[PDB]
């Protein structure tokens, strides 16, 4: 039936409807820190989110997305390994049922409690829908979350979850600044990959930040209270919405640091 994260429609089944699942540039991957090549030709990232306009938060049945106005160059990413301007369209997270798992990517096989994905699309393609069909159409910034101290900037997000508990619910979500979710350092790893959920298109330039941000136990707790199901359907907690690491195959992970 339709894809999800349960036993019967989980990652191991995806290839039946999305054959690209077994492609050559699938994500996520394990980042082997001793095999990643420091590349001094990589430029520093440029994050300009000062004009970011958030509009809405939505439960789509697999995660929650905070959506932004991408009608103009208001929140963009450039620099790093990228050519051109990438506009922020949305961010969402991947998390676990326990603090020992939840991230998509792993570092030296270590799993994090969650992973934030900031999704950007290449302005040269005019819209998101055309961008996903190109090898360089998307840029996704991945940020690891570990449990420790609370992240003040994530709290406006935690507090609205109650209102979008089930699939298809949405709430107005204006004036949220995504700068409150960045770590202090912008050192990163980069490799060519894909979306980590169906349709798994291989159109992503991944930018994974070396430094994790911390959230409190109580904050991740609230994530685990969401539902995969729609209102009036049997309750399935939204947990473990991450895909296991995929073979690197013929790809190199480059590091912006040493
Ligand atoms: Zn994601």
Image (spheres, rainbow, N blue to C red):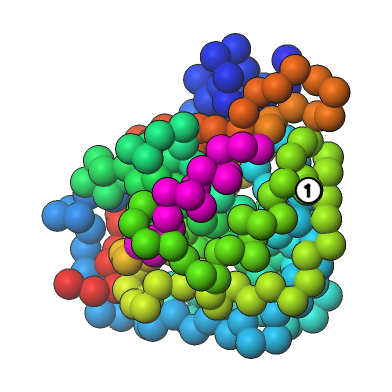
- At a point 51% along the width and 52% down the height, the residue shown is 219
Residue 143 quadrant: bottom left
Q: List x then y, in percent, for residue 22.
A: 49, 29
Instruction: Give whichever of 112, 82 is nearer the camera.
Output: 112
Relative image position of residue 46 (x, y in whole percent): 49, 84
- In the figure, residue 131 lies in which quadrant? bottom right
Furthest toward the front, the residue is: 218
Return the residue nearer the eye: 32 or 99.
99
Q: Is residue 125 above or below residue 96?
A: below
Question: Where residue 145 appears, x then y in whole percent?
Answer: 41, 55
* Residue at x 25%, y 41% (from the top left corner): 109
Residue occupying the point 64% across, 76% down: 177
| Disc 1 target residue | 163
Task: In the rendered view, tell whether residue 43 sits above or below residue 156.
Answer: below
Q: Residues within 10 Å of mark 1 (few under 14, many from 20)?
A: some
- Seen in the image, is 221 located left or right of residue 187? right
Q: Quadrant of the N terminus?
A: top right
Quarter where residue 55 is shown: bottom right
In the image, residue 154 lies in the stretch drawn in magenta: no
Residue situated in front as seen by the camera: 128 or 51: 51
At 33% across and 37% down in the image, what residue appears? 100
What range is drawn magenta here?
Answer: 212-226
Quadrant containing the C terminus is: bottom left
Looking at the rendered structure, the secondary structure element under dot 1 is: helix
Residue 105 in the image: state x and y as whole percent. Answer: 39, 46
């Amino acid at each position: 039936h339709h894809w999800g994260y349960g036993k019967h429609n989980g990652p191991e089944h995806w290839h039946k409807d999305f054959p690209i699942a077994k492609g050559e540039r699938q994500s996520p991957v394990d980042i082997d820190t001793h095999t990643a090549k420091y590349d001094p030709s990589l430029k520093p990232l440029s994050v300009s989110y000062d004009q970011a306009t958030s509009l809405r938060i939505l439960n789509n049945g697999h995660a929650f997305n905070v959506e932004f106005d991408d009608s103009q160059d208001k929140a963009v990413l450039k620099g790093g390994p990228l050519d051109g301007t990438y506009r922020l369209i949305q961010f969402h997270f991947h998390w676990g049922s326990l603090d020992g798992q939840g991230s998509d990517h792993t570092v030296d096989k270590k799993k994090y409690a969650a992973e934030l994905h900031l999704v950007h699309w290449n302005t040269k393609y005019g819209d998101f829908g055309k961008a996903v069909q190109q090898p360089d159409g998307l840029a996704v910034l991945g940020i690891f979350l570990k449990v420790g101290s609370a992240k003040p900037g994530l709290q406006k997000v935690v507090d609205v979850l109650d209102s979008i508990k089930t699939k298809g619910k949405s709430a107005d979500f204006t004036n949220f600044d995504p700068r409150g979710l960045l770590p202090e350092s912008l050192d990163y790893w980069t490799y060519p990959g894909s979306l980590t959920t169906p349709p798994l298109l291989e159109c992503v330039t991944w930018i994974v930040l070396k430094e994790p941000i911390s959230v409190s136990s109580e904050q991740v707790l609230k994530f685990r209270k969401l539902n995969f199901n729609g209102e009036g359907e049997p309750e399935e907690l939204m947990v473990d919405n991450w895909r296991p690491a995929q073979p690197l195959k013929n790809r190199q992970i480059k590091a912006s640091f040493k």
